[PDB]
Image (cartoon, coloured by chain):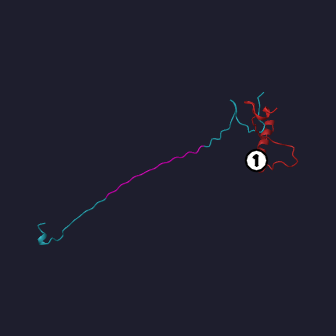
């Protein structure tokens, strides 16, 4: 005797020793990315090509 | 015979039971089974339990 068995219920595992089908379908995907930047450019100039007389000493 | 008609005894109560089944022997007035997949699914379950694998 295997005990009471439901008639219309779907066949499910209920006790120790019962079998069950596992459909292994795994799809995992993780990603991450980052960046940082900094820039600085500086140019400066001053030139006196021709200096008038009253400015010579300066 | 009035107290039995006016009161109820504590612990003497009724419960409700529910279940699912199939009714056969209809004269073409059953499920269409195209819009009710569970009818055919449970009929197949019963047949598999009885030893027939459709």
- Quarter of the image for residue B38 reads top right
Vertical comparison of B15 with A41: above or below: above
Determine the residue located farthest toward the top in the rendered image. Answer: A1
The chain drawn red is chain what?
A: B
In this rendered view, identify the residue nearer to me: A12 or A49. A12
The chain drawn cyan is chain what?
A: A
The residue at the point 13 percent across, 69 percent down is A55
Q: Is residue B54 visible?
A: no
Residue bearing the label numbered 1: B37
Vertical comparison of B8 with B40: above or below: above
The residue at the point 77 percent across, 35 percent down is B6
Q: Relative to residue A50, is residue B29 drawn left or right?
A: right
Magenta stretch, main secondary structure, is loop
- Quarter of the image for residue A16 reads top right
> Dividing the image into 4 quarters, which one contains the C terminus of chain B?
top right
The residue at the point 14 percent across, 72 percent down is A52
Q: Which residues are magenta?
A: A26-40
Callout 1: SS: helix
Instruction: Find residue B19 and report its horizontal and vertical position in percent.
Output: 76, 39
Instruction: Find residue B17 and report its horizontal and vertical position in percent.
Output: 76, 37
Does A29 lie within the magenta span?
yes
Q: Is residue B3 visible?
A: yes
Instruction: Find residue A30 and report its horizontal and vertical position in percent.
Output: 52, 46
Vertical comparison of A25 with A54: above or below: above
Circle 1 marks a residue in which chain?
A: B
Determine the residue located farthest toward the right in the rendered image. Answer: B27
- Quarter of the image for residue B7 reads top right
> Dividing the image into 4 quarters, which one contains the N terminus of chain B?
top right
Q: Relative to residue B49, is residue A51 drawn left or right?
A: left
């Amino acid at each position: 005797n295997y005990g009471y068995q439901p008639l219309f219920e779907d066949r499910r595992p209920r006790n120790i020793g019962d079998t069950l089908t596992i459909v292994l379908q795994e799809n995992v995907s993780a990603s991450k990315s980052s960046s940082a930047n900094a820039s600085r450019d500086g140019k400066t100039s001053f030139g006196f090509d021709t200096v008038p007389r009253y400015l010579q000493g300066l | 015979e009035r107290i039995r008609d006016l009161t109820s005894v504590q612990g003497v109560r009724e419960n409700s039971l529910i279940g699912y089944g199939l009714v056969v022997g209809l004269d073409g007035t059953g499920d269409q089974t195209t819009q009710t997949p569970f009818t055919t699914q449970t009929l197949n379950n019963m047949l598999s339990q009885l030893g027939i694998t459709v």
